[PDB]
Each structure stands twice: as structure tokens, then as C-alpha cells.
Image (tube, coloured by chain):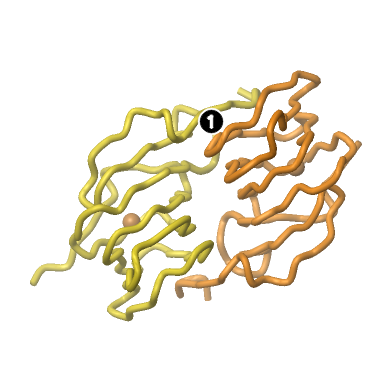
Chain colours: A yellow, B orange
Amino acid sequence: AAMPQMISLSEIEAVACPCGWAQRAFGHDAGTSVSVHYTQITKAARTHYHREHQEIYVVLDHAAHATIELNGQSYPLTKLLAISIPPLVRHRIVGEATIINIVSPPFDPADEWFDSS
Amino acid sequence: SAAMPQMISLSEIEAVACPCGWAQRAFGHDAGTSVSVHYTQITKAARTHYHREHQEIYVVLDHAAHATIELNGQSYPLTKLLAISIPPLVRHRIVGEATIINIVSPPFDPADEWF
Ligand SMILES: [Cu+2]
Ligand SMILES: [Cu+2]
């Protein structure tokens, strides 16, 4: 319970998600207070939001002109940009990118919501 | 209010000297998040330390050859994108040069550092 854990994000089996591929660590079973994903943005995705989870993206690399959209506002991605996304904030990434997604509390896939067209 | 998104370039934050090197700390206590994110450059030897009220997760972005992390007296090698969860009271430090992202929970408190 109070034991350190060690995981290689790059070696974790990658799973498909709407925006690309996710390598997820420290889920709810792990006892940690947050999940840590190493996520490859390869494809465009619906704008979405979370009702119970706040996310913090940390950009590790990105394609030129890649942006992030927060409540309909667009901002360019740069290296080591950190973005805090509280619950209810509509968000998505546009263009290719690699990020560390820090989720609290631990990530729960059930908590994904969309606005209709 | 912590209802609003926030945005900060870790590489542009004023670097603060800490025992192990230099830290660029974002989303501190006041930011209204549940965690702090530090972009920390480990450049020097540091005494083995521990935290009494804080979980830490290191994510190694880069490291010099043969660099290690020590946890409760055990040495393991560092590798790129190695993630280490360090619960409260786990004695630990990094030996050798490295660049990490340090995720702290609850938000960072500089008072909480022990020996
Ligand atoms: Cu999200
Ligand atoms: Cu520490």
C-alpha cells in the first residue's frame, strides 16, 4: 500500500483512444492519487469534457501549428507547455503531439462527455 | 476560482535552486489544482530525503549514463520515460544527472522535506 512503484511508460502496452494511442499508468488499483498517461495524439477527436476529473497535459513534442482548444479558444502547443484542465472545460488537441496526461483522481473512462451538434 | 483552465510554459518559469538542482514549479498551492507539476533538472548530489504528507511521481525525461534512483536504500537504473511513484515516508534521491517531471500530491509544500 505504501510501497513505491516503477513502470516504464514506453513499454506499457499501448491502447487505442479517440485521439490516438495511450500508455496508461497508476490506475485506481495502484493506490496513487493520480493516473499518468503517456499519450500519442495521432488523429482528430471530438471535443469532450470530464465531470469528475481534472487533467494536466504536459507537451513533450508537437507538430508545427498543433494547438489545444479550451472552451472554444485555440492556443498553440509548445515544448513543456503545461495545461490545467478543470472539470467541465471542453477540450481537445488539434494536430499531432505527444503528451503526459496527469489525471486526478485516477482516470475513469466512464467519465467522458460531449456536447451535441 | 479553479473552474478556469491554466497555462504555463515550464521551461520559462524562473528556476529555483533546490538541493538536487534547479526546479521550475507550476500549479503550486494557490493554483487551485490537486497536484503540482515541477520540471526539475537534477545537476548535483543531494542528501536522501523524504516527505511526510506528499505523494510524488517522477517521470524521467532524460538522464546521464548510469544514473540511478534510490528508494529505501535500493538502487535502480534510470531510463527514459521511467515513471516512479514515491509514497510518503519513502526515503529517496537521484544519483547522477537527469531531467524529470515531478508530480506532487497534494500541491507542493517546501516545508515538507525531511532527513
Ligand atoms: Cu480529456
Ligand atoms: Cu522528493
Give the amino acid at mark 1.
Gly
Of B14 and B111, the residue lying toward us: B14
In the rendered image, residue A41, in percent from the top left (x then y), is placed at: 30, 53
Where, quadrant-wise, is the N terminus of chain A in this rendering? Answer: top right
Residue placed at 39% from the left, 43% from the top?
A107
Where does label 1 land, which residue? A31
How crowded is the residue under tag 1: few (<14 C-alpha within 10 Å), some, or many (20+)? some
Left or right: A38 in relation to A67:
right
Residue placed at 79% from the left, 34% from the top?
B95
Which chain letter matches label 1?
A
Picture quadrant where residue A15 is located: top left
Left or right: A110 in relation to B75:
left
Residue A71, above or below B56 = below
Of A107 and B94, the residue lying toward us: B94
In the rendered image, residue B75, in percent from the top left (x then y), is placed at: 74, 21
In the rendered image, residue B114, in percent from the top left (x then y), is placed at: 88, 40
In the rendered image, residue A114, in percent from the top left (x then y), is placed at: 19, 62
